[PDB]
Length: 49
Length: 49
Image (tube, rainbow over all chains, first blue to last red; front, side, top):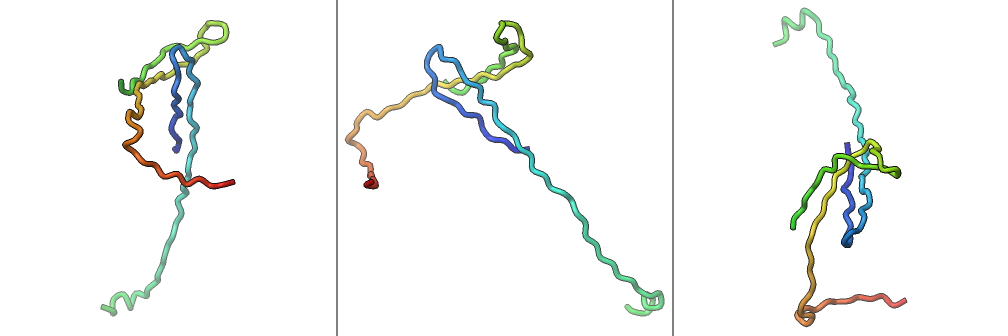
């Protein structure tokens, strides 16, 4: 979630205020995948050190 | 005085009955001015039309 600050103002005595509700936004980040694979022989897995 | 925040429990509408909303009121008091104008110097780079 993201937003900004409210805006103040210099007012006099008995002066009505004005609403200062801020606005909001929303960033988004998707999650993706990566992979690697290698096949080996049985004889080899036992011979190579 | 510093920053004070207040919680108004009940707002009204154009017919002086509750309209289902609340609020947060805040205010601040301070003031300043320059006493001796000759203890400063200010450079003014003004662009001719």
